[PDB]
Image: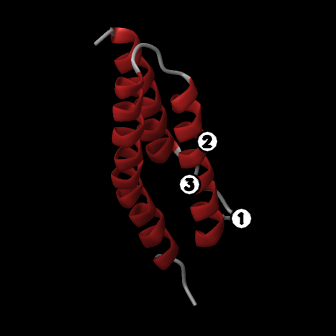
Amino acid sequence: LLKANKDLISAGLKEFSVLLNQQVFNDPLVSEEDMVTVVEDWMNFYINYYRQQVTGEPQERDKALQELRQELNTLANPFLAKYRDFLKSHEL
């Protein structure tokens, strides 16, 4: 209900999707642990962000927060892989 709610989600969606796909690949390169922290921060930051940026009944808010948590959890899986493979491509 209300395009406003779905709009906020889509914003976090396009933001994350574009962010993962628009990351910058330049040396020096960031490590996996550093990327993980950044990803986690992005995930908790967005999660808390959306829990407070909702309207209407509390039930809808929760569905947005739950779907988001699963949304990032899935969306992050492929990103970490791209960087994982990007890390392996190194030499040593």
Which of the two marks, 2 or 1, is nearer to us in this view? Answer: 2
Q: Is residue 77 above or below residue 69?
A: below
Q: Which residue is mark 2?
A: 45
Q: Which residue is drawn at the image coordinates 39% and 33% (left, top)?
A: 62
> Quarter of the image containing the N terminus?
top left
Residue at (33%, 40%) from the top-left corner? 67
Residue with the most extreme bottom position: 92
Q: Is residue 88 visible?
A: yes
User: What residue is pinned by disc 1?
Assistant: 28
Residue 67 or 41: which is nearer the viewer?
Answer: 67
Residue highlighted by disc 3: 39
Q: Residue at x 47, y 39 (%)?
A: 16
Q: Indicate the quadrant where residue 68 lies.
A: top left
Is label 2 or label 3 in front? Answer: 2
Q: Nearer the viewer, residue 41 or 14?
A: 41
The local crowd at label 1, few if under 14, some if 14 to 19, many if 20 or more residues have their Cα within 10 Å, is few
Compared with 84, 64 (above or below) is: above
Label 1 or label 3, whichever comes before in sequence order: 1
Residue 37 percent across, percent down from the top left = 63, 61
Which type of secondary structure does the marked residue at label 1 adopt?
Answer: loop
- The residue under label 2 is which amino acid type? Phe
Tell me the amino acid under the disc marked 1.
Answer: Pro
25 sits to left or right of 72: right
- In screen coordinates, is 8 left or right of 44? left
- How much space separates mark 1 and mark 3, taking CA atoms? 19 Å
